[PDB]
Structures are given as C-alpha cells and as structure tokens.
Image 1 (cartoon, protein in one colour):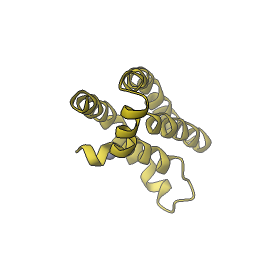
Image 2: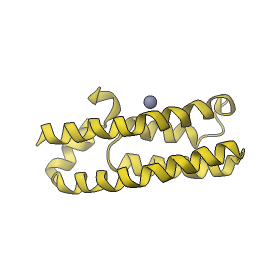
Image 3: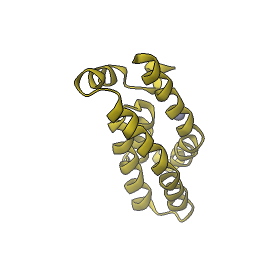
Image 4: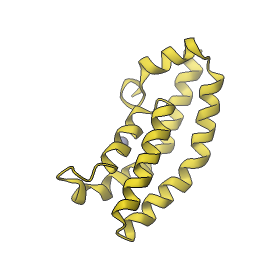
Length: 117
Ligand SMILES: [Zn+2]
C-alpha cells in the first residue's frame, strides 16, 4: 500500500518544492547502496555485534527517511532501539523482514512518483 510504505505528505511537498528528479536520483542511490547495508546488518547479527547492528540500523533509518520510504525508516528505528524490551527477540525478524522487502518498497515508490508526476 502507498499510504503505508511511503510518507505521502512529505513526498507531495518535495515534488512541489524540488521536483521528481532529485527524488528519483536519491532513489537510484538508495537502491545501489541497500545491498551492502543489508549484508552488513546480516553480518553484524550472526556475529552478535549489538553496537554494529545498531549502527547500520541508524544508517538505513537515515537513508530511507530521506527518500520518504516510511516503512523501512520505521524498521531501521526499531533495529536501532536496543532499549525496546523485545529488541533481543525480534531484531532478527526485523532484519530479515528488511531483507525480503526493501526492493519491493522501492518499486512502490517508483510507481508512485511516476503516477504522481
Ligand atoms: Zn515490512
């Protein structure tokens, strides 16, 4: 769903204040960097490197939010929050979930910008 995976209001504002090119430009940079980010999370997880997990989750949180991918930003926030009581149990699922869905979320943003312009 659009309203659920994307930050629609922020996106519509950017279309007006900046235009779609810088969005599609960011998207393209996001898409090429994600593979290495997920890998790093995956590796920090298996090595039981908490600080490492939290560092990469923050990085992805920042990157996703800049392009309006609200849902991925929300996952990165959880991954970077070890004060959450269920962090220990759930961090593995959040990372896997991110792994399986990031490309899909990117395809939804792309369709939206294409329709929105
Ligand atoms: Zn998800």
